[PDB]
Amino acid sequence: GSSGSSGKRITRPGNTDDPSGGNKVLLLSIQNPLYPITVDVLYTVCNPVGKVQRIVIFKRNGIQAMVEFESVLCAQKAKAALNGADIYAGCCTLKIEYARPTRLNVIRNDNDSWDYTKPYLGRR
C-alpha cells in the first residue's frame, strides 16, 4: 500500500511591470528617406547637440536607426533639438521615439552601424 498528498501554489517569475518612459536610447525613424541615410547623416546633426555613443541603422518596414546617448539627460535635449529637425528639403524628417530597450548591439563597424564609444576594433 501507499499514500501521499501533492499540493502547490501559483508562482510566476514575472514582476510588476511599468510604462516608465525615458531612456538614453531613442528610436529614430527617417520620413521619406529618398536619399541614402547613413549613420554620418545622423551623427552629423546629432553631435551638434551632444556626444553620441553608437548608431545602428536597420531596415525593418522603413529606414530606421537607433541612436544611444551618454546619459538620459542628453537624450531629453537631443530628442527635442532633433524632434522635427528637418535635414533635407521638406523631406527626410527625423521621427524620434523612445525605443523599448535601453541597450543596443553592434555586431561590426560599418556604414550601417557605427560604434564611437569603442573606435578600437581592428588593429590591422
Image: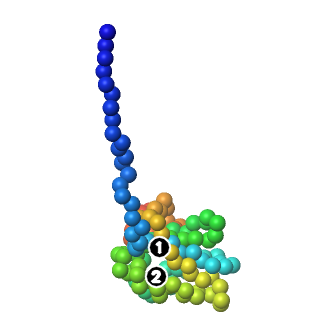
Q: Confirm or deny contact between disc 1 and disc 2 (CB under 8 A).
A: yes
What is the quadrant of residue 103 in the picture? bottom left
Q: Quadrant of the C terminus?
A: bottom left
Write down the residue under mark 1.
98
Residue 17 falls left or right of residue 92: left
Which residue is at 48% across, 69% downward?
Answer: 99
Q: Label 1 crowding class (10 Å Cα cut-off): few <14, some 14-19, many 20+?
A: some
Whole-percent x, y for residue 118 in the image: 39, 68
Q: Viewer-proximal residue, 42 or 109?
A: 42
Q: Position of residue 78 (x, y in %)?
A: 44, 83
Q: Which residue is mark 2?
A: 79
| Image location (x, y in percent) of residue 9 | 33, 39
Cα gap from disc 1 to disc 2, whole angstroms: 9 Å
Q: Determine whether 34 is above or below 12 in the image.
A: below
| The residue positioned farthest toward the top in the image shown | 1
Give the answer, above or below, for where 19 lies relative to 107.
below
